[PDB]
Every structure is written in C-alpha cells, then in structure tokens.
Amino acid sequence: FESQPCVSIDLRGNITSWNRAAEQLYQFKEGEVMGRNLVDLIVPPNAKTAALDTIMRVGQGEVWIGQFSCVRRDNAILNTVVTQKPILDDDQKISGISVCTEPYSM
Amino acid sequence: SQPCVSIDLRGNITSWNRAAEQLYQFKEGEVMGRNLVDLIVPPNAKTAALDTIMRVGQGEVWIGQFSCVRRDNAILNTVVTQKPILDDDQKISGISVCTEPYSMPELMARNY
C-alpha cells in the first residue's frame, strides 16, 4: 500500500528506495534510478545547494516540510511540497532520509 | 492546547499563549518583549539555538529537538515546530515556535 510518492536516500543523497507513486510523479522506474543521487537527478542546477543544505539538516535529526521544485523526466518543472524525515533503522540510529510528496502544490 | 510563542526577527517575544504559560511557567505580561533564547535556553545551548531558530525561510517548516529550561529550572527536552510569520506584503516579520508533544524519534520515518 502507498499513500503518496516516497523516495528514500542515504545520508549522501543517493537513492535507496523509490516507490510506485514516485515512478509516476517523476517518470522514472526504480531500477533506472537506484543508487543515483536524488538532488542531481531531479533538482534544477541553481537550486542544488539549497536542497543539499536541507538534506544535511534532516539527516542530522530534523523534519522539514516545504516547497521543492524538481524536474520530471519529460523536463516539466514540478512545484511540489515535500515532507523530509530522518529514517531510523532497527538499531535506532539515523540511516537515511525520507522524501515524500504531498498532494498540494506551492 | 498547544504551547505557542511568536518572536520578532530580533528574537524578542511578540505572543505567548496560555499553554506556553503552563509549559514554561511564565505569564504573557512578564515575557512580552523579552528575548526568547535568554529566557528559556540553557547558556551552553544558546548559540546553537540561535544558529537555527532564526533560519526559517518562506515556504518551509522545521521541526526539531529544542532544549529549554522552565522558570523553576527543570530541564525540558522538547520538540518545536518553527514556521515563518508573514506580514501584509508577504515578507517574513517573525517566527512562530510551537511545542509538539513528542520526542523526535516518534516523528521520524522507519525502516523494517
């Protein structure tokens, strides 16, 4: 079951999971993008530093909700709202970041 | 029900609700205009708090751990949601700092 587009990245920003709703939103299949860097894949070049700064704070233990402009496979610009969360593993340590897209645009 | 404090962009208190009076043990009248970080953040943690507490931009919300100290000097390990307050021209004019009743791990995502 999937409520929304969701992507998981490790602490460097490389993709570790990419759900079916993400396949539809961004127009890549999971196999095409596994291991690729999310910010390089979909964030427009002038916005990468800002996106990376957010991800760095999230990986250190904060939750973020905000405007997230990204580039679909077909080169449409998406003005999304995303919820970014640290992901905890079984050992209760931060292992990555969740990037989930909300149903309203900014 | 939710403790909420508003600050201006100097870090000084502009709003303090009844729930904040109960959480932190101060009344609105005595804290209005006071610097929030000097009021409730332990000395060792202030630069850290300042480093982030003023950094919220337009169209984002930050949720994170926030160590504070009550009037009685009990240490509180809290979580706060920080959002910008916009003026009539949609410029940031302040920051809203509202307490969540959870520790951070209860808000995080999980791998199984």
Image (cartoon, coloured by chain):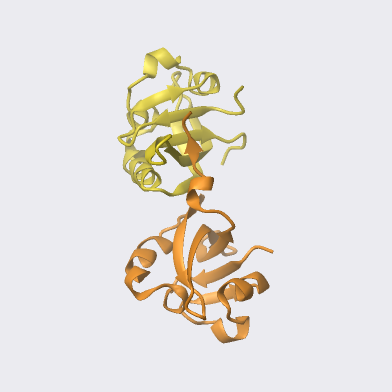
Chain colours: A yellow, B orange
As displayed, is residue A84 above or below residue B112?
below
In the figure, residue B9 lies in which quadrant?
A: bottom left
In percent of the image, x 52 and y 36: which residue is there? Answer: A80
Q: Quadrant of residue A93?
A: top left
> Which quadrant of the rendered structure holds the N terminus of chain B?
bottom right
Residue A106: image location, x then y, percent = 56, 41
| Frontmost residue, A2 versus A32 | A2
Residue extending farthest right: B1
Q: Is residue B71 above or below residue B75?
A: below
Residue A64 or residue B78, whichever sits in front: B78
Q: Tell me what residue is drawn at x 39 percent, y 65 percent.
A: B49
Q: Is residue A82 visible?
A: yes
Q: Is residue B16 visible?
A: no
Image check: B16 left or right of A85?
Answer: right
Give residue A71's quadrant in the image. Answer: top left
Residue occupying the point 50% across, 19% down = A23
